[PDB]
Length: 300
Length: 253
Ligand SMILES: COC(=O)CN(C(=O)c1ccsc1)C(C)C
Ligand SMILES: COC(=O)CN(C(=O)c1ccsc1)C(C)C
Image 1 (cartoon, chains in turn blue, green):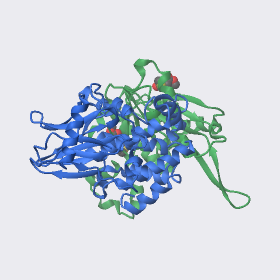
Image 2: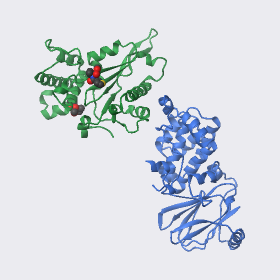
Image 3: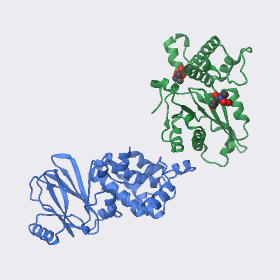
Image 4: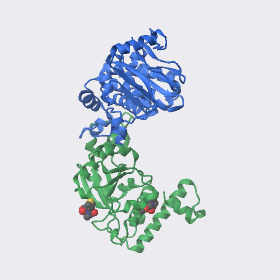
C-alpha cells in the first residue's frame, strides 16, 4: 500500500480519492492519504469550499513514482508533485503515519468497485489523452475541452480523446452509405478497433476514463465521449461476444456508482433509450438494462 | 437552418439551390391475394429535383426493378433518393453545383447529408412550407414519361415553360404552388379548369397551356376558388361568410 502525503491544507476543501470523499477544514492538520491499493490507477480530486467552480484533480499510479500534494498560494490550487529523493519521501511518510495525520483509503475487502470501474484504464493511455509529458501524473478539470469540441481552444490543455463522428468520411465507406450509417460494424471493428485502438481493451479503457472524468469533474466533453463510445457498439450489428458481455459489466458498475442525484446531468436519454430498446444490442446488455430500469426508470 | 416564410426571397437569389422531394419515389398499389391476404405491387416513381429560380426540373425516373429483392423499401427509398441526388451533383460542372439543397421531408436530411459528405460546403436544409410537389404526377406529360419508362432514366423539363420571359421567378414559383396545390386538392376539377378551352393548347415542348397574361389571371382565380370550395366541403364551412383576409390565409399555407 502506498501514500500521497500533503504538505498541509491551507484552504477548506472537499478531497476525493477514487469514489470516496471527505471534507478538510481551513488550516486543519491534514497530511494526506495512506493505504492506497497498489495495482490500479487512482484519482485525487478537489472542490474548494469557497468556490465550487474549482473542480480539478490528478490521475496517478504509485508504481511510477512518489507523489505528494502541496497547495500553491499563487495559482490557488492543490498541486501534485513528484519527490525524487526516496529516503526523504519515506522519512516524511513515516513521521506523518506515526502522528496519525493521514486518512486511510477506506476500501472494504468485499468491494471490487474501483477495479470494476478502472479494469482497462492504464496510466500510459491516460498520458496520451492528457498531454503533459514532464509529469508522470495527469491533471484534469471540469472545464477542459476535448479535441472534438475544439474543432466545432488552447491545444495544450485539451482532452485528446479519439474523435468519433457518425456522419464523417471516417465512419462511412463510399458505396456503403446506407449500410454503414445504419450498421456501424465497419466503423467499430475495422476503423476503430483494428485501426486506431488495436484491441478492445484499449477501447474500453478510454470509455472508462471518459466516464470517470464526467462523474468526478462534471466534465461535459468527457460525458459526450462516453456516450459516443457506447452508441458506436450498440449501433453495430456485429460485435464480438466477449465484447458485449464485458460492456454489460462495465456499464453496470458505472450506473451502479453514479450518484442518483446527478443522473439528470450524466445520462443522455436519447442514447440510453436507443441503446437499450432500439439498437442491434437491445437484448445483449441484460445486467445494465436491469439496473437502469430499477434505478432510473424515469429517464426511460 | 430550416426554410420558412421569414425568407421566401432566398429561394430566388443568385445562389444555386435545389429542392428535392421524395414523395413519389416509392409508389405502390395495395391489393388482395388469392388467399385473402394483402400485398403490394410497386409502380414506377420519380425524384423531383427543382431549381426554383430557373424552373429546371431534373426528373429521375425510379423504375420498379430498383426494388427487386430489397427489404424495408420505404427506408431504402430515402437512401436511393440521396444516392441519385448526389450522383446528379457530381455529374454537374463545378459552377453549376448547388450551394444548398432543401429537402421537403425531414426524413431525407440524414440520408442526403451522408451521401454528400464529399461536398462539405453544400448546405442540406429542411423547410417549414407544406409544398404540394407530390402533385407532380398529376402533370400529364410527367406522369406519362414515368409510367412508360422500362429502365432507369433521367428526363429534363422546364417546370415554368416560358413564363420567365414575362414574370419573375417569385411569381412563377407562386403560380406553380397554386397550380400544384389545386391538382393535389381536386385533380379532376383542376384539370378541367386548365384544359376546358380547346383553343388554348400545350406546346409540344411545354407542360402547361399557352395562356396569355390575362388568361393566367383568370386561371389563377379559378384555382383559388377551387381550393376555397374544397376547403368549405371538407370542413362543413360556409365560404360566403369568409373575408378576403380569411380566404388569403386559408390558401396561403
Ligand atoms: C430538355 O432539355 C433541356 O435543356 C432542359 N431544359 C431546361 O430548362 C433544363 C436545363 C438544364 S436542366 C433542365 C429545357 C426544357 C430546354
Ligand atoms: C414565392 O412565394 C410563394 O410562392 C409563397 N407561396 C405562395 O405564394 C402560395 C401559397 C399557396 S398558393 C401560392 C407559398 C407559401 C410557397
